[PDB]
Image (cartoon, rainbow, N blue to C red):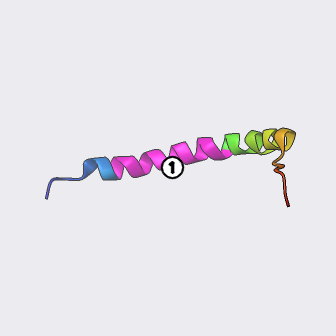
Amino acid sequence: GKIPVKAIKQAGKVIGKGLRAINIAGTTHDVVSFFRPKKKKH
């Protein structure tokens, strides 16, 4: 079966990586406002 230790350890990383992502998501949300999506239409 092979002990999937990496699986359990990987779950713990997501908790931290996700927390660090949400912290930066706030600033990124603003930056997007500077560019703003605008493509031609018909």
**Amino acid at pointer 1:** Ile
Horizontal side of 32 relative to 22 (left or right) equals right
Q: Which residue is painted at 32% across and 52% down in the image? A: 7
Q: Nearer the viewer, residue 26 or 12?
A: 26
Horizontal side of 12 relative to 22 (left or right) equals left
**Residue 41 in which image quadrant:** bottom right
Q: Which residue is painted at 66% across and 47% down in the image? A: 22
Q: Which of 38 and 12 is in front in this view?
A: 38
**Residue 31: in magenta span:** no
**Circle 1 crowding by C-alpha within 10 Å: few under 14, some 14–19, many from 20:** few
Find residue 38 and report its horizontal and vertical position in percent: 84, 49
Find residue 6 and report its horizontal and vertical position in percent: 29, 47
Find residue 2 and report its horizontal and vertical position in percent: 15, 53
Q: Name the residue under label 1.
A: 15
Q: Does the magenta stretch mainly form a helix, a strand or a loop?
A: helix
Q: In which quarter of the image is the N terminus?
A: bottom left
Q: Nearer the viewer, residue 41 or 31?
A: 41
Horizontal side of 20 relative to 25 (left or right) equals left
Count of numbered tags = 1
Q: Tell me which segment is drawn in magenta.
A: 8-22
**Residue 19: in magenta span:** yes
Q: Quadrant of the C terminus?
A: bottom right
Residue that lies at the very extreme toward the left in this rendered image: 1
Q: Which residue is painted at 86% across and 38% down in the image? A: 34
Horizontal side of 5 relative to 16 (left or right) equals left
Q: Which residue is painted at 56% across and 48% down in the image? A: 18
Secondary structure, mark 1, is: helix
